[PDB]
Image (cartoon, coloured by chain):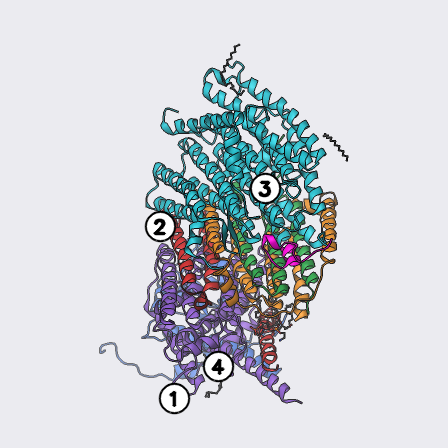
Chain colours: A cyan, B red, C orange, D green, E blue, F purple
Amino acid sequence: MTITPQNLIALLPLLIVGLTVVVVMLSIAWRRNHFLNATLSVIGLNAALVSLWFVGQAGAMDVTPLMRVDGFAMLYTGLVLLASLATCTFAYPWLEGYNDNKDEFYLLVLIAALGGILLANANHLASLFLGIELISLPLFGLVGYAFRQKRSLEASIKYTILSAAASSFLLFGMALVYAQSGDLSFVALGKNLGDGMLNEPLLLAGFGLMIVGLGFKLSLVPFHLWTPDVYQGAPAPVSTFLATASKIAIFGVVMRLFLYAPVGDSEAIRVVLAIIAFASIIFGNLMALSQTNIKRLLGYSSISHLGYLLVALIALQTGEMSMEAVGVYLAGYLFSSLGAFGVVSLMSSPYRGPDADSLFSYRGLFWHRPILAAVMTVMMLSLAGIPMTLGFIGKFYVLAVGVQAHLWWLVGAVVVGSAIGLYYYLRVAVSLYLHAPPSNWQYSAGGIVVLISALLVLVLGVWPQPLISIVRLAMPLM
Amino acid sequence: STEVIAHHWAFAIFLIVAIGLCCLMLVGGWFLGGRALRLSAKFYLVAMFFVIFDVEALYLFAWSTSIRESGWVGFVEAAIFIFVLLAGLVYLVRIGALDWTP
Amino acid sequence: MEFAFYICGLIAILATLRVITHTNPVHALLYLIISLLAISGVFFSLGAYFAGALEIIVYAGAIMVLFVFVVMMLNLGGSEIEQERQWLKPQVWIGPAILSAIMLVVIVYAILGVNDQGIDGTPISAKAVGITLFGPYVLAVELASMLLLAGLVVAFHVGREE
Amino acid sequence: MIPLQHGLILAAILFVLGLTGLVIRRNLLFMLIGLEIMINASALAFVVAGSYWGQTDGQVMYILAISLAAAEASIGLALLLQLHRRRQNLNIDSVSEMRG
Amino acid sequence: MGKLNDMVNWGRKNSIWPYNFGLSCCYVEMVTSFTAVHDVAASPRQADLMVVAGTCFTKMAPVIQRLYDQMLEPKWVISMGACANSGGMYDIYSVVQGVDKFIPVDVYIPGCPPRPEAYMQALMLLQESIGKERRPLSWVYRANMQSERERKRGERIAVTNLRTPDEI
Amino acid sequence: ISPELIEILLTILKAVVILLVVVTCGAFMSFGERRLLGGSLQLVADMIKMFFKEDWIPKFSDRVIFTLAPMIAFTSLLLAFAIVPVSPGWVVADLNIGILFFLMMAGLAVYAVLFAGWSSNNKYSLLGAMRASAQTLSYEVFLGLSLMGVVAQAGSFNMTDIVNSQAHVWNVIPQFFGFITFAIAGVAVCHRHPFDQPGYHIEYSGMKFGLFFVGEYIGIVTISALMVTLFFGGWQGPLLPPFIWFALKTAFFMMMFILIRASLPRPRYDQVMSFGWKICLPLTLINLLVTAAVILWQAQ
Ligand SMILES: CCCCCCCCCCCCCCCCCC(=O)OC[C@H](COP(=O)(O)OCCN)OC(=O)CCCCCCCCCCCCCCCCC
Ligand SMILES: CCCCCCCCCCCCCCCCCCCC
Ligand SMILES: CCCCCCCCCCCCCCCCCCCC
Ligand code: SF4
């Protein structure tokens, strides 16, 4: 398909982020200025975020055999851009203490945001694969950005090796699917079959290997073991980005894949995803019980919350409000993880050398950082699914969707995992309120970001109608 | 046909005769006659730059054989590709990654 | 044409098996280059002329050069590699080989139950790849340039010396 | 003339061999080698599938796959050099400081 | 068989690459030999002739021995000048008295220094020695050649009058 | 006995004739550059000495790598020559990939330098080989990009299509910057002597040294013939038979390489890296862009 100028209007956030990459790289080539390059990165991300409105004026259509732009694409592009802006905002105070180069961080964050936007607009196996790699490789750089630190180098090596293996699995599965189907478009995966011949073995095996790669990327059991190690070893703004934007973009493109594919409603694939979601919920809640480190605890939290999202995804073919539920849960989980990892990033900034620790020490935080402690306890209550928080609205959506489609094992899994989550999140909150023995406007901007996230979580927990209205407004092409 | 299979036979004969020629050259050489610091990281950097720019060159190889069929649209797309490539090259030059002299 | 496919596939399988079991890294990389040439011959036997050309140009001519360069820079004169031979102990390799054989059996069982009309081997030239590359698939081209830039920046930041 | 299942079986064999090499080797270099074998086998599978259907998308997916292979090899070898610089060994069992 | 050995020795004699490892004044004469006014027309591993041209000191002798050992068969040695032949005028504590104390020598050149035409004459002598002996064709009996002294005796003793030193 | 079998045998004989001629011209022009700075009897004598020299593989070195580096340095550029058309009806392989096969052979040919460096087992030799390999990577990064203007004007990768597209005007006139960048790249990746040393030929003795010597001069023959067939019409000429034109142009470029060796000094290594990464690569990209613009502008 050719590209008309209206298709370029639908291409707007991708173009603006790519031009931002080029401009930031040319500015680094001119002179290494940390403030100017961070400003250019956030200006480009804000420009893409506000160009989403001009994309919305254009309408839902297809720009390529590869990209399809609609309200679904706009919603997940907005979520990715919000996570990227928050990552840059948290990264500046952390990078102020980094004695080596600092602007390659912003370059890689921009490229990873570009991959997230491509995954948001994806309609093709080529675009899915390219978006996953475009997310993964800047994350290879960012997870080990402080490679002189031992844990950061360890996490970089682990994430690079395991993500290359997952990409190989995904690529081989896509190759088997293309061997069976003959077209790489999402709508044509299983279209040639019919009348009960949907469970073709090569198509199912290709989707299984794709599921292996994607479930690595989504921290789903049994491809989950990297998550606490990589989350702990990575720098804290990198942990923020890797928890929010990567998971959101990959789950959005997985939702598109299972919505458009005629094989997405296969009984075997549904049962396999049910087993993966059940094990993900239970294991990610059980492994976070005895966690004394906040980063590993949030990693197992990510496993459990992606399991809840997967439960919402299983009922996509049966129900109709599954896309709305996934959007509401993804907004809630985005703001919760942004607040939690932002508190961790602010208390670990500036980077105090590669030879020193990077620990958070959450005990007795309220007696010297009361606002951050309030934000962190609101985030822990939100991740527990407790009412008056947006995480409860997401959990309610997931349970309503599961009850509607008679997924009773998943409903019981959500209940049990929610109780276990209540235990460890409440332990973290009371540890914040127990007893224990900055000075620049970018740290203030990070604090403002986590505070606005906390206010959004509280307000949309006690009044979730605006979020539901703007999520139902984002309907994809049926 | 016969011309294409004749050229295939000629090319196969060329490859095997050249390889056998070098192999028997070494065989005759080995058979005849009597008998009685710290490696700098710049080499890895330039090799990796070669790998990356060779992949971009492969994309331009694909474009160059079908310039007329893609038209001015393909020219604009390839100009964007080449501009990103040149911006990366200017970046590598300016950060001293391609400067070998101190 | 099918003889070229079967011979090159056999050579690729044997060379890969020699790669994963060898102890000297240089000989392992040489066997890997041999396997890449065999896979390029497989590509040429299937009509994918551009794919085989890039298999020798890029995979066997750029990536393996980078691996060879790294092996040189490591100065491996028996630096805790050749002395161990730990992977040849059956308690180390028997389990993973069993697991990978089970995976191969499952994948082959999936493959054998597909409709097969055969590969005609009609040569798909690089002109068609360039037409479809800068036509329908051109956002893939631009974002693949961005992906290569990402790899460039990441590897430069990690692999400096200072 | 060449069955599609034969090319797919060849690609599956090479992918399985690459995965075995990735698992059984403690050396980081041979793990990167096994990763290259796996991604090249997946790219070969894409070429086989594209040549069966007569479409040009298989070689396009090959090109994207080898772009990923080149960039991942670059990043992995930079990480290997950093590990050899700051620990003077490439045994991956020693890189286990984060656990639990 | 007979013509084959002749062609092998012909190939060895018509292609000789010297490793001119000289140490003193004799080496500078051999540097002057390469110019276009004399028309005389590497590494020890591929060189087949070693031209030892200069004084073999007690400290330079291990270097000469190692550089000769690095060469490969067939190998030939030409000593140039009195120093390489016998130690020359330096019968002193710090000079090895002749390079043939530790490496075999195939052709000797008297002089101090020899002129480059003497080196070309020694190249001709070495070519004749190579062409007259024979080596095994595949995996050494050198020919006992007539000495140049007795061969040239008649035309040397037949000399009667020479130009006087007074004129030029 | 069939006419098809007669044609097959004639084509095989043509391929073997081309191979023997290119190898013999490599050896003969090796002696020619030796004498310019009878004689075939001297070349045969040198070949006999190389045959009967004691072939010695070092004790503390690998056997396979040390043996394989000269094999690469010979066969890579020989098979690179395997695509060059010398006359209508006189070609070894009329491949659809062509100049892609040349790029394949060059990318395999860097392994000769790398493997000689590994099998040298000397720190100075290994460092010099790392420098030489970095140089040939820096100058083969743009070899295909310099040829891409010619490929764009021809619209194909076939060499016969290229020399047929050079019918009205030789490609040296439009693709002049492509010509100079291909000349510099071919000079540097074949280790000609503005760029011969930044040595890795040490510890090679007898037949392996002869293989390196003959292989690099065969690479000079191959690059000269490719220069002719890519920028100077190939076989095309007004009056003379086509092979005579091809042979005289190829011999002119071999003598041009001799003059280049005898007429240029040695740039420093840093200058060589800076040139190959700052001037030639952007020049090749800009030349390809301008060539595409002119091609699309003229074909209204
Ligand atoms: C040290 C040596 C180790 C061993 C090396 C390999 C030895 C054996 C190689 C030769 C095997 C026998 C001949 C194989 C068939 C030759 C003909 C052929 O490939 O034809 C197929 C195809 C023709 O297509 P075409 O004419 O363009 O289109 C018309 C319609 N198809 O044409 C093509 O597809 C052409 C492209 C394939 C050409 C392959 C050439 C050889 C590749 C390996 C080079 C090895 C170099 C030395 C080692 C490097 C470092 C390890
Ligand atoms: C229910 C959702 C979250 C609401 C806000 C949670 C609390 C935010 C911080 C408010 C101030 C807390 C003060 C705690 C003082 C503890 C004193 C203990 C004395 C023994
Ligand atoms: C340096 C030149 C290398 C050339 C390699 C190929 C040689 C092929 C020789 C073919 C000769 C006959 C060509 C057809 C007849 C036209 C020419 C007649 C007068 C020579
Ligand atoms: S023989 Fe005479 S000229 Fe030669 S090195 Fe000895 S002192 Fe010098």
Residue C116, placed above or below residue C20: below
Mark number, residue A422: none
Identify the secondary structure beneath mark 2: loop
Q: Which residue is mark 1?
A: F239
* Circle 1/circle 4 CB separation < 8 Å: no
Q: Do tags 4 and 3 sit on the same chain? A: no
Identify the secondary structure beneath mark 1: loop
Mark number, residue F41: 4
Compared across the picture, whether F239 is left or right of C41 comes to left
Instruction: Tell me which segment is drawn in magenta.
Output: A175-196
Dot 3: within a 10 Å radius of its alpha carbon, few (fewer than 14), some, or many (20 or more) residues?
many
Dot 1: within a 10 Å radius of its alpha carbon, few (fewer than 14), some, or many (20 or more) residues?
few
Compared across the picture, whether C43 is left or right of A406 comes to left
Q: Which residue is mark 2?
A: B101
Identify the secondary structure beneath mark 3: helix
Mark number, residue A217: 3
Instruction: Give the CA distance from mark 2 to mark 3.
Output: 43 Å
Q: Where residue B27 sits in the image (x, y, percent)?
A: 61, 70
Q: Where residue B29 sits in the image (x, y, percent)?
A: 58, 70
Toward the viewer: A104 or C64? A104
Q: Do tags 1 and 2 sit on the same chain? A: no
What residue type is disc 2 on? Thr
